[PDB]
Image (tube, rainbow over all chains, first blue to last red; front, side, top):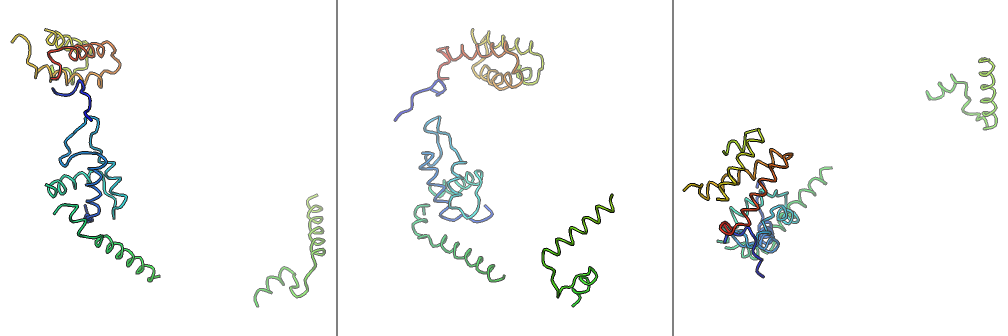
Length: 154
Length: 77
């Protein structure tokens, strides 16, 4: 497929794991469809490092910013591809990332491992605790008190 | 001319500069392609940003850009 001609055609604090570098390279190659040197093939397909940062952060051990992803690609992967990242990824056999998760599980396990006088006030009120009043009598006392309060108010 | 396009606040000055550049483009008596390009790029950057409300100035500049793109000599430059 050849794009049609237009009027404008001129006639890092945590270390990067091999899985992160591999995701970065594969995002740039597959999604952006850009070459190693990011030379523009189609004018509309300008590099999008936000998408690459999103792809890398799907499996990264820490948030990688778009600027960090661009800097890493240009300063490591281009010189490395010019052992290749694919060869290092194949030889690692996921050992480093497995050991990372083992270490995290160990830290989480470490954190998990590191984990009478009452009658006096009734007698002052006038309540014989040992001779309960049934609810009918208490309701009658409430009614009498309310009636006396109403009479006092009147 | 570049400082007039960039900093000058008077829209009449900008219209005069655009007229001068249009006369130059539509014509050693005329500026080189590099000078025309510099002036047109400065106008493209500052005229719209500094004078959004001036419809006549923007129309004159867009008419000049239209002539440039219609011109066969400058096509593909």
